[PDB]
Image (cartoon, rainbow over all chains, first blue to last red; front, top):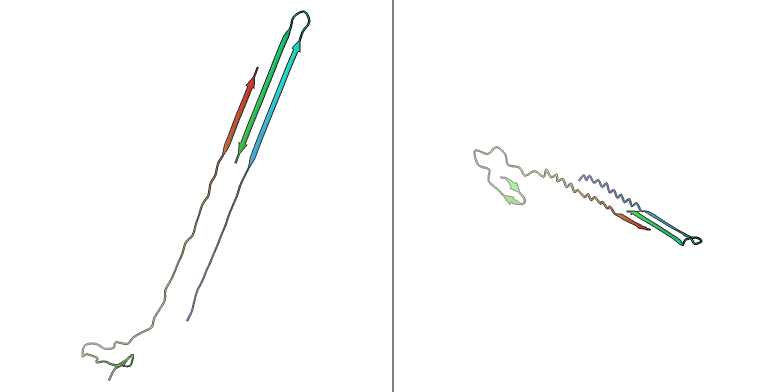
Length: 49
Length: 49
């Protein structure tokens, strides 16, 4: 009474998470001979999963 | 006389020998396999002037 068993269990799990966030704000104002106003806004968002 | 499993049998004139043989072998091959994949990409951009 011979027997012959073989079990080869394999489990692999990989997870990657990346997030990028960038924001820039600039404003300039000059009043003297003539009033001057300047505004600048920049926003960047990047996410990888 | 001919005995097979406590039962009296008859051997005909053409049959040379009819003997029960055990001769047992079974094979059982099971397969299991899974594959996962995920992807995500967030993109956001803002500009103001």
